[PDB]
Image 1 (tube, rainbow, N blue to C red):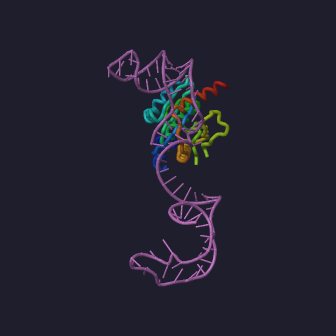
Image 2 (image 1 turned 90 degrees about the vertical axis):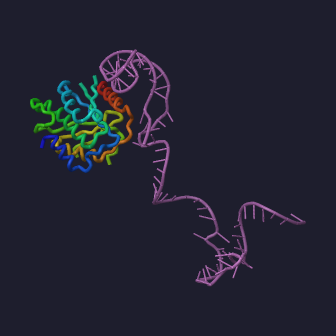
Image 3 (image 1 turned 180 degrees about the vertical axis):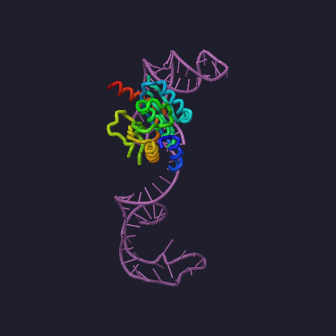
Length: 183
RNA sequence: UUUAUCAUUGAACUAUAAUUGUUCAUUGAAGUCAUUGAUGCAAACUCCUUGGUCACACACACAUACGGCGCGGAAGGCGUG
């Protein structure tokens, strides 16, 4: 069923300690929009539940860095589902204008970055040949949302992070801007 | 468990406040590597060097507590010439 509250409760029910937060946890998702306004509307509707400390948005001055810190395993599912389905529904189904409902025929596709010093010991695959110097890129392909919620749970249940610096985010911004400036 | 710069300028910002606090960018200055590090605690495992792997024994002892009553070797203490 293509409603993310229903899947979020579905995965709160059954996933063996999905509430617990992962220590040292950092996810950076750089996204692009051609409308600033509707994207800021989505971030407001998102921040009403996500909370300011766990999820942040930094605009480069269109590119917006969406950063998750200290997220729960359940929390990452909610955020990445809303943002990837928004990024898709801008092109696919523009009229519907609901944030928490993902219309049929949307397959979630995107990429996120984790810090390089994670140890992992499907639908989310890590990439060979990653352009950013100190970060690892992961790609999610063709997930319905029910399948993507499940796959994020099986992915961040395993992975385990370690000891990033305080200003690691500024470093990611600087390096990402250098590569796209070079191209 | 705990750590990862300093100064200048602009912008928003909280405020009893010159704007003390918070975030973003800019110029200059240094800057051991590390963060899979460092520090605290503890355990298992694997492996190296070293030795009289000597002789006679497989033995019922002992209150003054224990024949120090086999041959060597190592190291000291003390005595004599």
